[PDB]
Image (cartoon, helix red, strand yellow):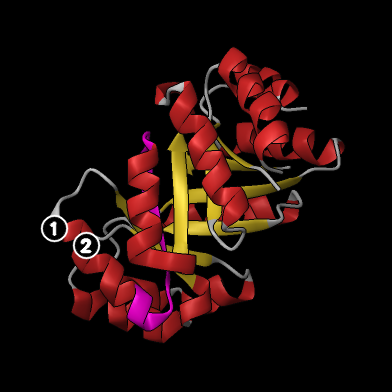
């Protein structure tokens, strides 16, 4: 399996390092999903995460525009940072970022709870070959619709603690049937996180788990639940 640490740029850089160290001590790939809330501290985290042995880094661009990313593109490239655009910008801005970084280092990210604005971004991303990530997914109907609109560019962020058993099994089956689809399992509850492992081993299954690094202690025990 792989563990993704989703943090803001302002997380105490110490705690992320121990979590990265703890995960690497178990011989497991660890990724960093970093919110670019402040650029200077984001770069400091990127350097710290790289030195701690992170497998890779995804930068959630947040409110950063094209000009902001331009000033740090050399730093992003030298550290191999993947860009996740928050879809608060217009198609002109998203196309500019995709053209700047390349379609294969860029992902369109949006909560499924959007309406027609959700569908507008998927079509543009599909044309550009950019992967599109649907977050806050809880029902199989949402996953099936995302597969219909996005095809093999689809990525799903599944809210495990808010997903019923039937939807969890169906979404896992959909991912197994469509292996090019990226499936990410956001987990906080220890019992439910262990539950996915048992269900996934019967229905599917690599597994990517998305964790918060708010407190180191619960994150360790959460990592141990996923083994």
Judged left or right of residue 81, residue 162 is left
Q: Residues within 10 Å of mark 1 (few under 14, many from 20)?
A: few
In-front residue for pair 95/10: 95
Q: Which residue appears farthest toward the left when viewing the image?
A: 116
User: Residue drawn 54% across and 37% down?
Assistant: 185
User: Residue drawn 25% across and 67% down?
Assistant: 121
> Which percent across, then down, holds residue 111?
29, 47
Q: Which residue appears farthest toward the top when viewing the image?
A: 191
User: Residue drawn 77% across and 32% down?
Assistant: 22
The tag on residue 119 is 2
- Quarter-wise, where is residue 55 in the image? bottom right
Judged left or right of residue 99, residue 201 is right
- Quarter-wise, where is residue 129 in the image? bottom left
In-front residue for pair 69/29: 29
Contact flag, marks 2 and 1 (Cβ < 8 Å): yes
* Placement of 125 over or under 16, stated as above or below: below
Q: Which residue appears farthest toward the bottom when viewing the image?
A: 99
The residue under label 1 is 116
* Placement of 176 over or under 84, stated as above or below: above
- In what element is the residue under mark 1? helix
> Which percent across, then down, holds residue 86?
31, 57
Magenta stretch: includes residue 35: no
* Placement of 62 over or under 111, stated as above or below: below
> Which percent across, then down, holds residue 80?
61, 70
Location of the N terminus by quadrant is top right
- Quarter-wise, where is residue 79 in the image? bottom right
Magenta residues? 126-139
Q: Residues within 10 Å of mark 2 (few under 14, many from 20)?
A: some
Magenta stretch: includes residue 130: yes
């Amino acid at each position: 399996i792989e563990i993704v640490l989703a943090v803001s740029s302002s997380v105490d850089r110490k705690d992320v390092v121990d979590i990265i160290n703890y995960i690497n001590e178990k011989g497991i790939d660890v990724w960093l999903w970093l919110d670019a809330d402040k650029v200077e501290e984001a770069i400091e985290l990127i350097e710290e995460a790289v030195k701690a042995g992170v497998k890779g880094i995804v930068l959630r661009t947040k409110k950063l525009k094209l000009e902001d990313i331009k000033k740090i593109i050399d730093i992003l490239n030298k550290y191999g940072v993947h860009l996740l655009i928050d879809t608060e910008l217009e198609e002109e801005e998203i196309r500019a970022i995709v053209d700047l970084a390349g379609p294969e280092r860029t992902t369109i990210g949006l909560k499924y709870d959007l309406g027609e604005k959700r569908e507008r971004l998927i079509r543009t991303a599909v044309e550009l070959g950019v992967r599109v990530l649907l977050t806050d997914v809880t029902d199989r109907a949402q996953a099936a619709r995302g597969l219909a609109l996005a095809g093999d560019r689809l990525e799903l962020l599944l809210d495990v603690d808010r997903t019923a058993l039937a939807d969890l099994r169906a979404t896992l089956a959909l991912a197994a049937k469509n292996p090019k689809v990226g499936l990410y399992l956001r987990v906080s509850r220890v019992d439910l996180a262990a539950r996915v492992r048992a269900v996934a081993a019967e229905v599917a299954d690599r597994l990517a788990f998305v964790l918060d690094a708010k407190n180191a202690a619960e994150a360790k025990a959460l990592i141990d639940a996923l083994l």
